[PDB]
Amino acid sequence: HMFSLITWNIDGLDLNNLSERARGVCSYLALYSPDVIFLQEVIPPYYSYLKKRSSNYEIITGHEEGYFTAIMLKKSRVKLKSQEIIPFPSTKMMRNLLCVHVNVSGNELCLMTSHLESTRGHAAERMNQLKMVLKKMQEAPESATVIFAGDTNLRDREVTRSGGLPNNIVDVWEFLGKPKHCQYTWDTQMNSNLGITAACKLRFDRIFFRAAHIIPRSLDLLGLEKLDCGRFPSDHWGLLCNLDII
Ligand SMILES: [Mg+2]
């Protein structure tokens, strides 16, 4: 009846206090108990802690070495059907789109995650990767509900310069009337995990939707509380999305 996903860039590259951060993120995931979990910037040790703490989830990794994405499926409700790792072409950061075809209740789904080129890379390649994600979203089978969710790293109206969004694809944040409480997924003013003195408020973590059923209900943020070490679980904010399986 209900349906929930959580997208989070756990910032696994920040090695400081990584144990307590992983314990906190696992506490959030265990508390909300979502059905699908999209994780970005996961390192093998973090993946080992996740697999150790989350046994009721099937974890599909985007790679093996370095950092990668991961998709966790609640085994008690989400039935894995297929998986495909679509690698980006001119990628200078070893990033790819992780697609996982699943079945929830009686509906088919296509859950996609990605971690596009970061701020240090080439914004043009980030736009190209966005076009590849949207194209792979449109070319999905005309029977499943495609749901993308991940750290897009987009800024400076790159969605408009990349040809815009197609007619059958919409941003869940924009669909809900652009709620201002979950307006920014990366805030250097409230989140003090990079030491950036300047206040840069951007919306990196995003969710794209298309259907052939499922309705986005609510949208929220998580990971806003400081841990015992005085740091947040990540430099990005978690993005919780609740849906209704009509
Ligand atoms: Mg990072």
Image (tube, rainbow, N blue to C red):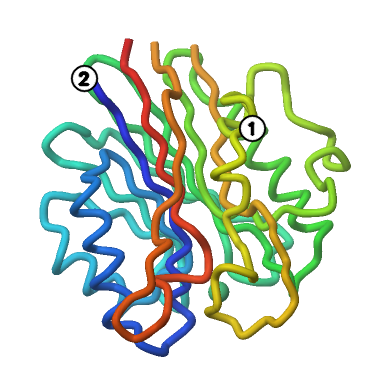
* Horizontal side of residue 77 vs 127, given as left or right: left
| Three-letter amino acid code of the residue under disc 2 | Ser
Q: Please tell me which residue is depicted at 44% across the width and 57% down the height of the picture.
A: 8
Q: Please tell me which residue is depicted at 60% across the width and 61% down the height of the picture.
A: 186
Q: Quadrant of residue 246?
A: top left
For label 1, count other residues whose C-alpha is less than 10 Å away and answer few (under 14), some (14-19) or many (20+): few
Query: Is residue 81 shown above or below 15?
Result: above
User: Quadrant where the N terminus lies?
Assistant: top left
Check disc 2 and report its element: helix, strand or loop.
loop
Query: Is residue 117 shown above or below 65?
Result: above
- For this orientation, the residue located farthest to the bottom is 16
Is tag 1's residue or tag 2's residue first in the polypeptide sequence? 2
Q: Position of residue 11 (x, y in %)?
A: 47, 72
Residue labelled with disc 2: 105
| Three-letter amino acid code of the residue under disc 1 | Lys
Ligand 1 quadrant assignment: bottom right
Residue labelled with disc 1: 178
Q: Position of residue 53 (x, y in %)?
A: 15, 65
* Horizontal side of residue 198 vs 229, given as left or right: right
Q: Quadrant of residue 122?
A: bottom right
